[PDB]
Amino acid sequence: RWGTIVSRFKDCAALATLGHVVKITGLTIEEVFTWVLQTEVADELVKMMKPG
RNA sequence: UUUUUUUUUUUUUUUUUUUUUUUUUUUUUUUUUUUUUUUUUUUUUUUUUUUUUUUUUUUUUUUUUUUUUUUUUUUUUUUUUUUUUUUUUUUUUUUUUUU
Image (tube, rainbow, N blue to C red; front, side, top):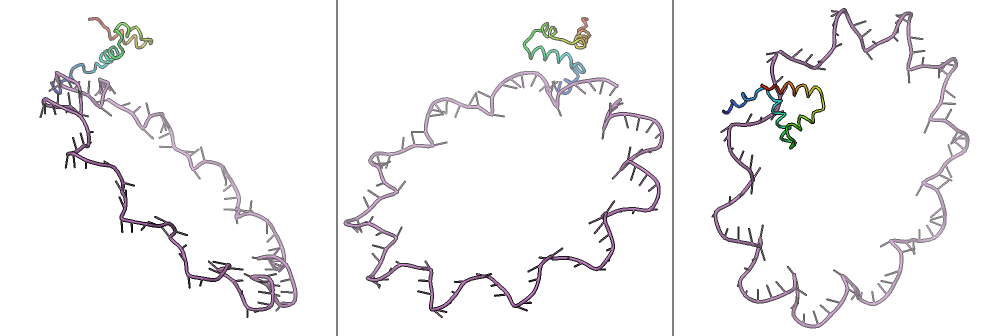
């Protein structure tokens, strides 16, 4: 698995960004989504939260 | 084009640890890096006290003149051929951006 780890979650850095900002603040995920105050960021989050 | 911790094998997280220990203390004594004795200006022969003086003197003044380290005369941008006056310009362009 040395060398092959860079294949996992390739070109998917925004999910890791969301996880890091959830863990580094101590807030729940709903509060992290609540504290967003821009329409562009909210639209990207909505497009990133496709259910299936 | 695609990407976007010059992050990541999994584990881990004191550049901690045999055990025992803790004045880079200690033989016992001792405790002026004091002392023969007796002395105590790194004073003194007696004289003496301007590292003063022959006398005379006293601008490290002076021949007499003189007194811009001025001057042929003419002059007075260390200006000028005329023309000119971004040490601008082919056209097109205008992140020393980009699969």
